[PDB]
Length: 98
Image (cartoon, rainbow, N blue to C red; front, side):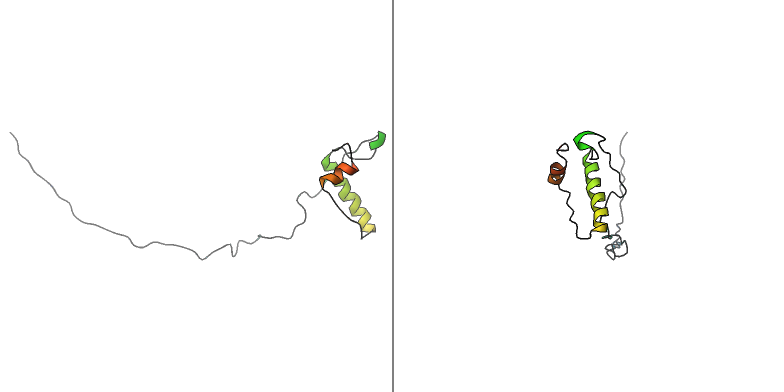
């Protein structure tokens, strides 16, 4: 024995209603360009205790802190004083640090 048939389909739908937003471009986020001149505040310097380096720095951090603190106190007494921290300054002042 054989013989059968069925089929059905109907309908179609759409939703043309998106929700975009473009009304904000960091206008209230703030803190874009804050007034700062340092990025490692508070420091110390380790020193040599004897020989031709007595009272002179052990590291590149110690040498930069010495230049900055020496100049800050000297220049607090002497407001004309110059300041420079390029690698050649550290080599030329502290020949062991090169």
